[PDB]
Amino acid sequence: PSQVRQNYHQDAEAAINRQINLELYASYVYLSMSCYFDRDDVALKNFAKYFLHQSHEEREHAEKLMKLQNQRGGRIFLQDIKKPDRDDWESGLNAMECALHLEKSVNQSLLELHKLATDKNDPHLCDFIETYYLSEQVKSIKELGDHVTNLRKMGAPEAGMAEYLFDKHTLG
Amino acid sequence: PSQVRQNYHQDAEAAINRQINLELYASYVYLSMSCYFDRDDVALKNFAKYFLHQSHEEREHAEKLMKLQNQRGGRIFLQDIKKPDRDDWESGLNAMECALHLEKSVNQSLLELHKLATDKNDPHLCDFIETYYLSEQVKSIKELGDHVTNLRKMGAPEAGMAEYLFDKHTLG
Amino acid sequence: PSQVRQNYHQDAEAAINRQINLELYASYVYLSMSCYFDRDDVALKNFAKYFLHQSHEEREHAEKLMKLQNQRGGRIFLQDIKKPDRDDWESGLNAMECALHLEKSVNQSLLELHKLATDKNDPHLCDFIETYYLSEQVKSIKELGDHVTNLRKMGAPEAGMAEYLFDKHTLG
Amino acid sequence: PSQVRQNYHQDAEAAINRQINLELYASYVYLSMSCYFDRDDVALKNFAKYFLHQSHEEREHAEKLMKLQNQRGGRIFLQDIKKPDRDDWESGLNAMECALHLEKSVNQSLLELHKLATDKNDPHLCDFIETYYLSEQVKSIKELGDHVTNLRKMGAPEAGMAEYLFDKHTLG
Amino acid sequence: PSQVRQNYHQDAEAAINRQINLELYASYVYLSMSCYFDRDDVALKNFAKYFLHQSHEEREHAEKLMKLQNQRGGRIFLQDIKKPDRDDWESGLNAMECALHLEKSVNQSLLELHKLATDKNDPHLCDFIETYYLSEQVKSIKELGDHVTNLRKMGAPEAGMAEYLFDKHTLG
Amino acid sequence: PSQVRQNYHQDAEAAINRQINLELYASYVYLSMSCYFDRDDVALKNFAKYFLHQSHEEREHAEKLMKLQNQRGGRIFLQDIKKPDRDDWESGLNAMECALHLEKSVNQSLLELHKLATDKNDPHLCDFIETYYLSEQVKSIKELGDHVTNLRKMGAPEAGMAEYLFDKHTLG
Ligand SMILES: [Fe+3]
Ligand SMILES: [Fe+3]
Ligand SMILES: [Fe+3]
Ligand SMILES: [Zn+2]
Ligand SMILES: [Zn+2]
Ligand SMILES: [Zn+2]
Ligand SMILES: [Zn+2]
Ligand SMILES: [Zn+2]
């Protein structure tokens, strides 16, 4: 046992490692979307910038979970970061819907992690999750939902000017 | 074929995708080392900071390779980022030796990529590799070799003060 | 032979003169597009400004090639700058497609020039081409491809608001 | 007929297109002279800089004529820019004499254009010519005459120090 | 073998050591010229300053090659720096011609070194040579050719005012 | 005889030329030590920086001596700069001991030169030596002796942390 470990269940450690992997995977998916929108035949610079920012924020979230794991004396065990489920995201609207789904799944994983921390009576872990990940996830999901709503109302993807003007105005 | 693609062989595209994956893997390995040195029972803050910086630089290298792939009209195809070969790096000296080996392998991959670009007469790709990756790799390998040499001479790992003072002076 | 001439093949000199002419011709074509978009019945100020900037950059490229020719002791031999293949570019999208084709042809000529310099073992000439023209051409071709993609998706030229809003947002 | 066109004769439009071509040709001749003086075996940096400045000013004059053509609703029709009558300008004094002759011919063409505008009672065109081109040409011709006079008195070209010290003092 | 050595042929190491010696020798020759022009019976302060600057730049080039040798894990092997071919450079024009010849020979050695690096497929070495030495050599040879042209046409050395005024104007 | 020469014996001129050569040789030896400590398997950055500074100071000393030679109307006669007695300096302590020996030998040569200037009653030369070289040599020898003493007491070379911490603290 780590000299610093206290009130840190093994299941919480495993859940934190899994969450680390999931945040790294979300960072990778956002990197994939940024790459897709930097394509010459997509060429939506602000979509690419937005998703690159999301990828960097996901990487920061994973690093914060790593710091938490070390703080509590748990041991980080890294897994393979699976490739994103696709390379062609096919539109700004589809990319935003997939990002919304990804943020909802990351939020569900964080909610399950908070439930586990609550069951194991790990108040520091619960507080960490709710302070640094749950509110961030709710804000991110709301922002992604707003983006999806606006893109759909604009007529995306069929309305060709829709994604371009959303890129300039909302994301630019 | 991409509207922008010109003098960009398919083998060069595949090699660039593989290099993207390798740079992402190196970033992941450096993140693993940073996590290891942030452990309470390792507690080498400057080793962790140095390897986190290496991880971020590797991620930037992968991002620049993907920007190159999009610039040339190639399509980025992301693969699984394999987990690092180990989670316990066991010492500052061992971590530096593994980082040296990783940078040498990344440099070897970049050299093979430059050879491929030369064979396909892709001067832009060759020049890009040279200006942004080969000199960086040579500098990184030299810095890692210096770190390893200094740690060895200081008596790392068995000289307990060696890694601590190297952390303070060289990496701090 | 020039007192400064060294490792500068006659074919390299001729290729550099031809490239000078081609860059001057591209500058002239971009001037033609700028003139077209300054027309009262086209009236796309940012398209005109963008293509005038391209014309000035092309003139700078030709002047840099002339400076290179004098640096290496070759003699600049100027030819007629042929008129652009048309005076009516008929749309922002068509002008962007023609600019993309022109930059691709300039890049192809630069690639052939780099191949010639490589065959004649003129490393300074190869390095000059790849440092100052190849990366610039790749960036320009990518930017033009992005412009063309965005204009096409916006519905240009048929979508009358497409070129106007692209002029304001992307080019303004 | 252009929506903006009024009191703009077809002959004025053709004369403006011809003047555009002539100004582009003068810019090209000045570029040739700048290139000649950048030669290693001529090596008069201030002569080259002076003639490059003349080339850029000629290009600006051509661009202003194009702006005038579009302002009046005339259509710019670009022609081949003929190569300068020679590549070897053989001296600072000879280059200055050729520049003087070129500016006198450009001024003669501008005077014929002003006569045409006067005959067709195009007061805006006459005023444009006289405010932006005639005074500029008179000043340029006077400056070139001064340069030629000083170079001749200094003993150019046979006086070896003459062109060097003129380059340093007058043009530097 | 050095821990950092990778894709660094022994012939490249030997060629780099020879180039180091040649750059040190060129620095020594430039120091000799600076000394000659600081003589009371020569007394060309700007010629001496120019050649001292050349000597310092040559020493910097040798030091950069030394840094490259250490970066690649090659071992620097210093040789005797041969005395310059003469102590009396006899004139500003003769010194400039000898400097031109020396820079051309250094450039030839660098070109052979780049050819060797190309044959050994050492892209980092080729890139290093071309980015830091080949363009510098071309610029230096062009500047020296310009100096020689101006001095010759000013009447140097027989025209006694020629070297003095070149010292004041071009070199001052 | 030089027009400026006065009270400047031929033996003093020869001794000054020999001192030129000796200072250039010391600069070369210090460059060799700097190169040795920049090696990846030595990797003592501050030792390398210190010895590079010593090399540059030795070059400045030689340059000052040749300025003195020209000031007095003597003629500088440069000789071969012999390669340093070794390429492998094997240690920070050994390099410091060799630097101490080299500074002591340079000081002995300067003392013999001052004795010669005294015998020839050349008060300006004696004053120059004592003002610019003797005090500098005494300070340098004392600093090198301090460095050697501290390295020996620290346990260099066998104490592996000794040279590293001396590099950080004294030389950093
Ligand atoms: Fe300490
Ligand atoms: Fe809008
Ligand atoms: Fe003067
Ligand atoms: Zn990398
Ligand atoms: Zn170009
Ligand atoms: Zn004009
Ligand atoms: Zn050099
Ligand atoms: Zn000294």
Image (spheres, coloured by chain):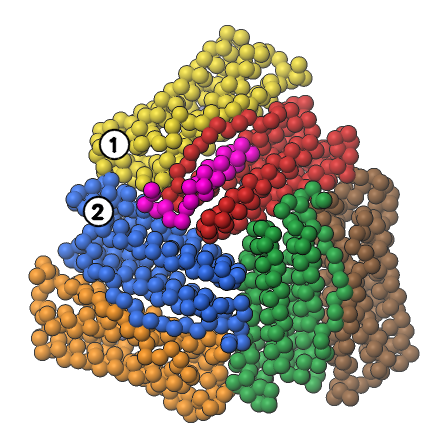
Chain colours: A brown, B green, C red, D yellow, E blue, F orange
Depth check: give the residue in front, B131 or D12.
B131
Measured as percent of width and height from the top left, residue B78 is found at 75, 59
Residue C25 lies in the magenta stretch: yes
Q: How many marks?
A: 2
| Residue D49 seen from this side | no
Q: Main secondary structure of the magenta part?
A: helix
Q: Dot 1: few (<14), some (14–19), or many (≥20) neighbours within 10 Å?
A: some
Which amino acid is tagged 1?
Pro
Query: Can you identify the residue that label 1 sits on?
Result: D157
Mark 1 close to ligand 3, CB under 8 Å? no
- Chain under label 1? D
Q: Is residue A6 left or right of residue F160?
A: right
Q: Is residue A124 left or right of residue F93?
A: right
- Indicate the secondary structure of the residue bearing disc 1: loop
Point out the stretch of residues depicted in magenta: C1-27
Measured as percent of width and height from the top left, residue D146 is found at 30, 27
Alpha carbon separation for disc pair 1 and 2: 19 Å
Query: Can you identify the residue that label 2 sits on?
Result: E163
Assign ligand 8 to one image quadrant.
Answer: bottom left
Residue C67 lies in the magenta stretch: no
